[PDB]
Amino acid sequence: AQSVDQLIKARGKVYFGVATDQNRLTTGKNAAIIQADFGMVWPENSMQWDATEPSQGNFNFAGADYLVNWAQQNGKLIGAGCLVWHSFLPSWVSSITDKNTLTNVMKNHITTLMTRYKGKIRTWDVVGEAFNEDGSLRQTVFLNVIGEDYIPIAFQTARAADPNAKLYIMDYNLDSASYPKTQAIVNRVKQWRAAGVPIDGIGSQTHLSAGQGAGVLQALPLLASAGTPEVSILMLDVAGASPTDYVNVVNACLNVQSCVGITVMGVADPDSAFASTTPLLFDGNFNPKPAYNAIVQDLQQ
Amino acid sequence: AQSVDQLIKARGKVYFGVATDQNRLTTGKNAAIIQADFGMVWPENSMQWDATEPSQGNFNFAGADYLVNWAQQNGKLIGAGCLVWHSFLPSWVSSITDKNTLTNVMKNHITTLMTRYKGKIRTWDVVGEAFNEDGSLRQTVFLNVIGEDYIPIAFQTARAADPNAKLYIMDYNLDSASYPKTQAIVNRVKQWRAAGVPIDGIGSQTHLSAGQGAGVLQALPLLASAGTPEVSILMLDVAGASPTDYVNVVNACLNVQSCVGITVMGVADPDSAFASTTPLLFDGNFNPKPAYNAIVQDLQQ
Ligand SMILES: O=[N+]([O-])c1ccc2nn[nH]c2c1
Ligand SMILES: O=[N+]([O-])c1ccc2nn[nH]c2c1
């Protein structure tokens, strides 16, 4: 099976990547497929807040360390995240009500994780899912306690911790150009960057239903109009794994100059959180599915 | 699918169990299958030394806590391990050369883990893979630095930390009654128990090639002749997943009064470390394989 990462690099992009973690790399055929076919790895779960700081100051890095070392040994780029994401917060964080304390807790979490891997991580997802569907800011503990400046603070802190990393904000339901959330994140990122906030990229969490790939062809250029140096496609999977949907997403990447690459959410269908929708590029026997071969043919042209 | 755990309990045994961990419970159909069909869970990796104490005295319990909570919420028994196993040691341990220091480090590791989960764990695998294939003791850091007393110390320390748990020694290649390692572990366990060492069980790590199930019918009664209150089948998988091999292992369990149950290495073939041998009871689409149905029929007859 030809390598989608090699082929996308030949078209001028940076990577075709995949999310993984230690117990994937030691089972199935995941390591062999990643070695041959993908150019970047992300930790699925091992870098999230609940996995890395389950109680205050008690950092759990064993799983993340394994993935970083494996990637370095095998010549792969590393992306990591998410530093600030309400969905993976442990209870001790969401109980904090003092603005000074929560600011320092957020800063220490960012600084500790980024310093540990300083210079080794290409892309950090710093803030995730900060927007409501109507485009207002999501009322998470960080917004409620710190206020809207928590986003500037997070990015400023991350830039100081590792100036080499590309810093991204990420969100989902940015797959349609007419959806209010898509326009809102563009407007807010434009404003933040105009005031000097170091947001290098917007990452679109592309968890799609059948037939939604076509809309990404119009949504991704819109996200790119915010003026960040980079945009990316993250967490990609498609219910039913139709070649048409997957090829449309790949072509959206190719059409947007600032889109650096694509990361799929897993290797093989049985290891998806959405396994009954068989939404990935390899089947339960680790054979490439028609969508994989269709991407290969699209990138060869 | 009828539950092998309910059927084996109806035959007078304690459980039919499976190894798992957090990211299995959140993907595929693993949680649903475990809820319906298995009565005990073990952490595959999250309790091993390299996952729980990656630096001296500094413990990581996020993954293990998740599995213990999940098991309690779903009414499942819990087994855990391995407290002392050379294959999962961090480098900081294997570089210790002082007998008193290594003894204290080992005792602290045992006591900290077992205290955290005191009263919640049915079975602890305390020492693993302590024997060479010829029956002599494996020359790990523990044997080289502490000496052969490390095994009595480990069990004595474990009994004091949680007197409710059943304490096991485990090894592999105990599948043939005429293999030297099988008789050696019997010899040594008899001696240790005569000296008052609290070894409650021998666990046989049953990682089998095709056709090796039949030999377990003679090996397991031999293991039971050491006189421990319990024996168990652990880490069970069979290359090719022949019904004949799986049924022979199940019947060995039924034939040995002190054998309390069986634990299979995982749920579905693609998540095995030996996936190309398709050695588990569910396939890559999470359908029960012929071996599963054969076990069901064997337990009903
Ligand atoms: O692209 N990704 O698959 C991915 C997975 C988990 C993440 N956490 N933060 N960013 C992430 C990206
Ligand atoms: O039975 N088991 O699958 C199993 C898995 C991992 C272990 N670590 N210690 N004991 C273990 C048993």
Image (cartoon, coloured by chain):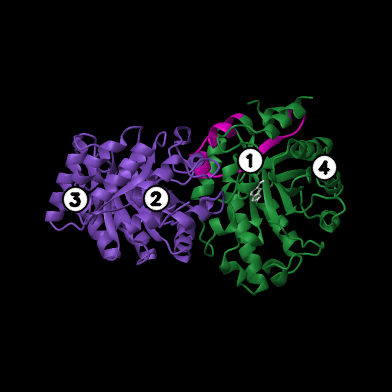
Chain colours: A purple, B green
Q: Is mark 1 within 8 Å of ligand 2?
A: yes
Amino acid at dot 3: Asp
Which mark lies nearer to you, 1 or 3? 1
Q: Is mark 2 within 8 Å of ligand 1?
A: yes
Q: From this viewpoint, is residue A203 visible? A: no
Q: Residue A59, how many percent across, how many down?
A: 43, 57
Amino acid at dot 1: Val
Q: Within the image, what quadrant is residue A236 found in?
A: top left
Element type at marker 4?
Answer: helix
Q: Which mark is residue A149?
A: 3
Name the chain under label 3: A
Q: Quadrant of the N terminus of chain B?
A: top right
Determine the CA span between mark 2 and mark 4.
Answer: 46 Å
Residue range in magenta is: B8-36
Name the chain under label 2: A
Most extreme residue toward the front, as rendered?
A301
Left or right: A195 with respect to B84?
A: left
Of mark 4 and mark 1, the one earlier in the sequence is 1
Residue B21 painted magenta: yes
Q: Which mark is residue B138?
A: none
Q: Within the image, what quadrant is residue B288 found in?
A: top right
Q: Residue B129, how many percent across, how many down?
A: 72, 58
Check whether the beta carbons of the residues at disc 4 and disc 1 lie within 8 A of each other. Answer: no
Amino acid at dot 4: Ala
Q: Which mark is residue B214?
A: 4
The residue beneath circle 1 is: B18
